[PDB]
Image (cartoon, coloured by chain):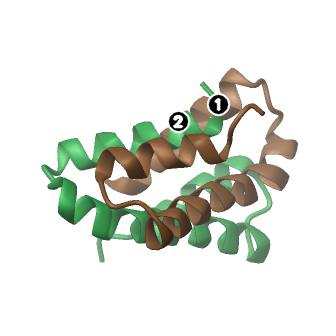
Chain colours: A green, B brown
Amino acid sequence: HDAVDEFINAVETYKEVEGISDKDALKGLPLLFKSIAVVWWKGVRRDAKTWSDALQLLRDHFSPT
Amino acid sequence: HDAVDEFINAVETYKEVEGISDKDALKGLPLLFKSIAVVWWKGVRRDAKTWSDALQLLRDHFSPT
């Protein structure tokens, strides 16, 4: 139940829900989740001041519009 | 159910299971999950050749010994 196990569950859930192949996943998912993680950390070191505002922020950054 | 939502669930599960405060979590968890993500990507661009070997790898890197 450590952080690494929860990280892997996220990646594997996403691979499953999106029906991504093992080959496309190996090629693509490490950089995608690396980008998410960097953006989250970047937006906390820049702006966010709260825990709820650190979560919400990452969403608004990957926004539908 | 996108990647960002699964990422947030991982972080929030970890915060909950470990009983981390909002203040310690804001300060600490973005860099921790950023590190995990970087290590995973690093170990795929270096060594791993398979999907099961990309998962397993990240574990062995955060190894108990």
Q: Position of residue B21 (x, y in %)?
A: 83, 34
- Whole-angstrom CA distance, mark 2 to mark 1, is 6 Å
Relative to A8, does residue B46 appear above or below in the rendering? below
Q: Nearer the viewer, residue A25 or B20?
A: A25
The residue at the point 20 percent across, 54 percent down is A22
Letter of the chain that mark 1 sits on in the rendering: A
The residue at the point 49 percent across, 38 percent down is B9
Q: Nearer the viewer, residue A23 or A45?
A: A23
Residue linked to disc 2 = A6
Tell me whether circle 2 and circle 1 mark residues in contact (CB < 8 Å).
Answer: yes
Identity of the amino acid at label 2? Glu
Identity of the amino acid at label 1? Asp
Residue linked to disc 1 = A2
User: Are both tags, 2 and 1, on one chain?
Assistant: yes
Q: Position of residue B43 (x, y in %)?
A: 52, 63
Q: Position of residue A39 (x, y in %)?
A: 58, 72
Letter of the chain that mark 2 sits on in the rendering: A
Inspect this view and state whether residue B27 appears. yes
